[PDB]
Length: 162
Ligand SMILES: [Cl-]
Image 1: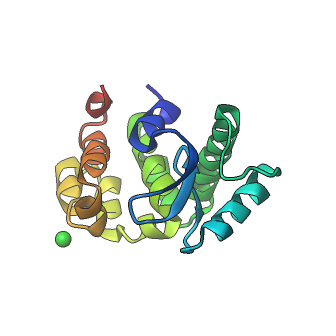
Image 2 (image 1 turned 60 degrees about the vertical axis):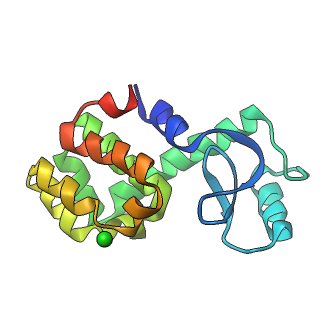
Image 3 (image 1 turned 30 degrees about the vertical axis):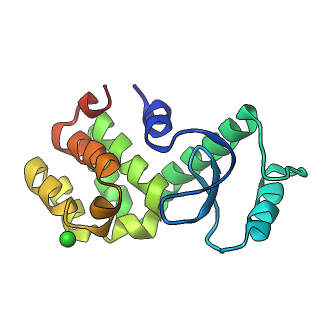
């Protein structure tokens, strides 16, 4: 199990523009295109990202390419973030994957808002952190996915995903 397989499980793979859980236009493996109500804007963003006239449809290869870019961006983003970096550095490999998952899903800013939970991860207080992170909008909106990530942080293993 690795980050890609993990996220592939949590986001799925769609080759046609779609609405994510909050109604935003997305494609591929959880690649957000735009937060605008317009499919036109979405289709525009899509072409800009792929570099071709897509007409809201991409190929597998294209979906995987966007995915490679997003994971890399997430990692670099974490490593640049003053708040996130220290947390990342203090963790074991599995739990680092869990932090990357959250960043991929909600952005650095969204994650940075788990101040309290993050501080607990840093102090290796596994159970407390899990309980705290569950008190969030994130958990209430996508509970099964949140549960999988939370268990990953609590246990440091891939169980939730196997
Ligand atoms: Cl709550």
